[PDB]
Amino acid sequence: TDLLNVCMDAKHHKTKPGPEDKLHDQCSPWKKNACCTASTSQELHKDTSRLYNFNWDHCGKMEPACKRHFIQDTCLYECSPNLGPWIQQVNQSWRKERFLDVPLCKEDCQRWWEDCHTSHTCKSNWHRGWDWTSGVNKCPAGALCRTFESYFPTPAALCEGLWSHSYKVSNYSRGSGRCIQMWFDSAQGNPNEEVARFYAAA
Ligand SMILES: Nc1nc(=O)c2c(CCc3ccc(C(=O)N[C@@H](CCC(=O)O)C(=O)O)cc3)c[nH]c2[nH]1
Ligand SMILES: *[C@@H]1O[C@H](CO)[C@@H](O)[C@H](O)[C@H]1NC(C)=O
Ligand SMILES: [Cl-]
Ligand SMILES: [K+]
């Protein structure tokens, strides 16, 4: 119960979730109850935003169909008040907590992978090892640009590995209430509230 409606202790996160009428674009589905501020939501839509100086186009321009998923993931990461059950203490410099093994809906993972499989990257883990000497992440020594499929032969590889096991792939479907959706419309509420509620009780 102490795992429901909480914000993890990380760089830009608010202390406690609450309404944010002004959440920008892709993050707007979180507007009734968010862990991110309007400002965070607008900045995260920008290329190489000031949140992390992370450049999605480290291997040329990433296709929009692909980039929207990375934006969506960052919406979830910054805004979701429904990941408490997967929050772990990590004592890193830019976050005391992160989430780990969030049961991501199979199809969200599949779609992410399919939409990105033509785009390019130089690394299978995007958390550690970038060349930051320019102030923005660049491909480090030994890292060649390749298709996403090269670094991520399956959707599970992408969803599980790219952010250091933030997610595990869940064998449940999107409306099931047994897996976290990265994409949702929420007109009838945030579907992930029920998911957190369920796993908290296990
Ligand atoms: N699910 C999810 N998880 C995320 O983390 C995330 C992010 C943040 C990504 C990010 C990547 C690299 C570094 C960075 O600067 N890395 C350094 C080392 C960092 C350190 O000191 O620990 C590097 O080695 O390149 C810092 C932050 C955006 N969307 C996300 N979605
Ligand atoms: C995943 O779900 C499908 C049905 O949707 C099922 O056939 C399969 O057995 C499941 N996988 C596992 C390992 O349970
Ligand atoms: Cl489409
Ligand atoms: K959520």
Image (cartoon, rainbow, N blue to C red):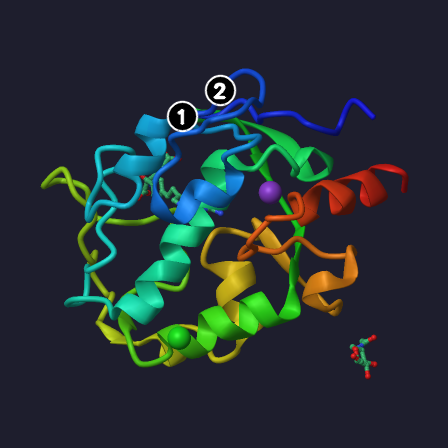
Direction left: furthest residue: 134
Q: Residue at x 82, y 44 (%)?
A: 199
Q: Check the image and name the residue furthest to the front.
A: 187
Q: Amino acid at mark 2?
A: Lys
Q: Earlier in the sequence, mark 2 or mark 1?
A: 2
Q: Where 103 falls versus 170 (above or below)?
A: above
Tags 2 and 1 touching, CB below 8 Å = yes
Which image quarter has ligand 3? Answer: bottom left
Quarter of the image holding residue 105?
Answer: bottom right
Give the residue drawn at x 16%, y 66%: 61
- In the displayed structure, 65 sits above or below 8; it is below
* Amino acid type of the residue that numbered disc 1 sits on in the rendered structure: Thr
Q: Tell me where residue 115 appears, x and y as whole percent.
A: 40, 75
Image side of residue 95 versus residue 48, left or right: right
Q: Secondary structure at mark 1?
A: loop
Disc 2 target residue: 14
Q: Is residue 155 left or right of residue 66?
A: right
Q: Residue at x 84, y 44 (%)?
A: 198
Tell me the residue that label 1 is attached to: 37
Specify few, some or many for label 2: CA neighbours under 10 Å numbering under 14, 14-19, or 20 or more: some
